[PDB]
Image (tube, protein in one colour):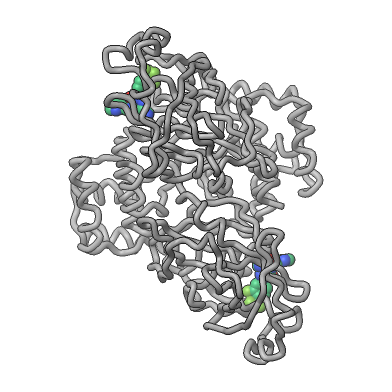
Length: 301
Length: 301
Ligand SMILES: *C(=N)c1nn(-c2ccc(C(F)(F)F)c(F)c2)c(=O)n(CC(=O)c2ccccn2)c1=O
Ligand SMILES: *C(=N)c1nn(-c2ccc(C(F)(F)F)c(F)c2)c(=O)n(CC(=O)c2ccccn2)c1=O
């Protein structure tokens, strides 16, 4: 029994985190084979940050300005390169600890583990979700840039996220490992608008299912509803619209609980309309939208 | 910015988790040097579980009944031993991956990371807290026994917890690594009472401080209070009494926020008495008691 926000085991990623310094700027990098990856705003400086010309700044740069360190070992930069907003520092030594990996760009609503790092030293691991505004609410202090997000699918590490910046709003933005931001964001010290964050309806329903499997079964209504009717209740409460693909993903959880998706959506409606009246579900007085249906099955089975 | 429940990086513990099987019973063990540690109820069977005589069951046991496997390697049990509720299976091969470690019995209110394992394979990591009833609310499916809780203090792994059982109540009980249960609990399939779980007042105050550092500053009252007066409000709401040792631990967080401990305790009182009125703090509509003052500093600085 039990349901907690759970991150993937982080050992395979710890061995990959190096330090990268440039001028008065130290951040984290990711070392896979002979390439270190890190955010390219490591070559910036104060007066550059408003609208840096990264092409020009990179031309002025000498490998010697690239201080790559793994543990107390210092690595040897044998060249540089810019792929979108990511810098690829090629090196002589290949990482002996390089796991089977791949780069994936994830979709709004998917979750990942974050290994928060400082100075190339792992500090802690926690679970995040890519919101529909392509932000992540995170825990990133100063020096945290270059920390990565990942899933462990089989034995394969699927890197999906590299942290770049905290928006003046207090939420976090970053890129995939090919250097393309999630969202409209650019690596410039300018005010940037994140969109409206809609609640991930399919994640909330997966959680209610986790609740039923862990005992909490008070929210159940014995009513019913239809897609169109629930979705009307969804735009009212800034909930992502539900699709039949969503219903289809929830099916295995439906078969285990004996609870049909539409019957659950009907339970959701009343919590949106009436509320929780001080009751709680899986320890929370709020509806949680950061477990995917896959997360819930991973734990609850 | 940001504050999330964060576990320690788990790599140093992953290398230590083996499989242990006995009869139709498979669970996890912890391999440090030439000793594997695991819960002793691995030698039980169905009819034994109501009141097992572990001495007698262990005498009937032959190393051959102890199937220890790390990865696809199968290890060689060269003897057995019972230390309280823990079984020590000595082996020929010492673990090359054994970190600097120590065994610590933690106090109610302290936190630790749990590496949830199945069949000797790490599945995920999350943060727990030892409650005053010496339970932990966890996420332990079947086969999860032998999973360990730990802190990373310096480079040293401090193992504090080994999971043994889920109480008919839905919460979890276990031992330290010398095999002494936390709490009044025994490894018998009998109904066992956990005590009243009092909220960890010093943890709640550490969180409110984390809130102030992350922007949330609405709960602040501009009132004040005294120990004796707040503690009266604490027994009313089943909150652990506050001591001057508690005030002393909160001091560094006091100096960073410019907020005095008693002024914060006064803010707490009004949230206990009036409530949150639908507002929220660090994302929650509930008061969170599973960050220690040390956890909060670790992240918020
Ligand atoms: C992470 N390592 C980190 N990154 N920045 C930073 C600097 C410049 C840009 C640019 F140019 F816009 F792309 C960024 F996106 C991100 C950074 O400033 N800090 C320090 C920081 O967060 C901070 C905030 C307020 C006051 C002091 N420091 C980083 O740690
Ligand atoms: C963990 N590996 C695990 N442990 N038990 C278990 C068995 C016996 C005792 C004893 F004898 F009381 F000490 C225990 F404390 C714990 C266990 O039963 N399961 C399976 C389980 O949790 C379960 C519950 C309900 C229905 C089916 N299975 C374990 O996984």
